[PDB]
Image (cartoon, rainbow over all chains, first blue to last red; front, side, top):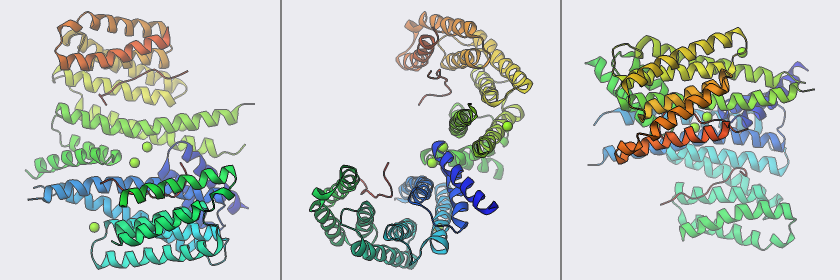
Length: 231
Length: 231
Length: 11
Length: 11
Ligand SMILES: [Mg+2]
Ligand SMILES: [Mg+2]
Ligand SMILES: [Mg+2]
Ligand SMILES: [Mg+2]
C-alpha cells in the first residue's frame, strides 16, 4: 500500500514535471517508479522515453557542438575544449548506462505483449547507439554489436507479431536503418531497410482508420525523407 | 599565475557551455570566475547574466506551471503538486540567493564605471524581484523593499551618468516599471516610469549612430508594448 | 492576460 | 550534411 501509493505519486510527479519542462526531474521520478517492479502502461512507457530522450538529447547536442569545436582546434592550443567535451561525454555515458540498466534489470522480459517488448528492445538499441556515437575503438565495435543485437531482436518480434504499418514497428525500422547508415557504415543495408519498410507500409495504408493513418504516415514521411537524403 | 590561468580557463569553458546550451554548467563556470576577485568585462558580465537568466528562467517557468495546477486543484486531492511546487520553489530561492550573494560579495562596488554599477544593481533588483514572485507574507513585503532599493539606486546612477537612450538605463527602467506594475501593485507609477523613459529616449533617438539606434529602439519597443498592455 | 516584457540582454 | 531522422514518440 505504502509502496503502491508511492508508485502512483512518482508517476503523477513525472506527469507534472513534463508539463513544467523539468525533464531531469521527470526522468528521476520515472526511474523511481520503474524500480517499484510494476509493468509500465503505454502512457508510462512514453513518459519514461520522453524524459530520458530530452535529457540525453541535450547531452548529445552539446557533445556534437563541443566535439566540432575540438576537431576545429585540432586541425592544422588550450586544453579547455577537450577537458569539457570529455566531461560531457562521461556524463552522457552515465545516463545511457542508467537507462540500459533499467531496461535490463526491470523492463525487458520475454513475457510481455509484442508492443512493450519491441518498445524496450528498440530503446535498448537506441541507447547503445548513443553510446556508439561517442565511442572510438574496439569499444565502439562491441557497442555496435550490442545495438545491432537489440535492434534485430526487436525487428524479429515486430515482423512476427505486428502489421507493417504499426507505428512502433515503423519507428524501430527507421532507427535501425539510421544505425546502419551512420553507425555501422552499411549504407546499402540502410537504404534497403528503409525502402522495404516504407513500401510494405504503403501497401497497407488503405486498411487503416483515420487515427492509425495519421500515426503511420508521420513516421513514413521520416523514412521517405531519410531515403531522399541517402540516395 | 595558476590563479589567473585558472580564471581564463573558467571563462573559456563558460563560453563553450553557452555554445552547447549547457547553461547550468555555464553558470557554474562563471560563478567560479567571479570568486577569483577580478572585475568582469562587458562580455563577461553578459556571460554571467545569460547563464543565470536561463537557469532561473526555467525554474520560474516551471514554478508558474506548477503553481497554476496547484491553484486549480485548490479551487472548490493528492499532495503531489504542492509537494513538487514547494521543491521547485526552494530550488529557485537557492539560485536567487546564490546570485545575490555573488553580487554583494564580489560584484557590487561604489568604485566602478557607471555601466557596470548599474548593471549589477539592476541584476540585484531583478533577482529580488524573482524571489518576490514566489514569496507571500511579510517576507514578500521585505523582499519588495529590497528590490525597490536596488532598482532605485541603479536608477539614481543611470539618470546622473548615462544618456536617456543608453540600453542599460532603458532595460533598468523597463524592469523597474514591471516591478511597479506586477510586484508592488503600483500601476500608475509603472505607466508613468515607462512613458517617461520612452518619451525621453524618443527625444534623443536622432543623435544615435546606426548600431546604438538598433540597441535602443529594441528596448523602446518593449516599453511601448508594455504601455499598450497596461493602458 | 499576457505578461509584461522584462529585459536583461539582447537575444 | 543534415542528419537523418530518428523517432521515439510523436511530438
Ligand atoms: Mg538542455
Ligand atoms: Mg571519454
Ligand atoms: Mg530548462
Ligand atoms: Mg516555500
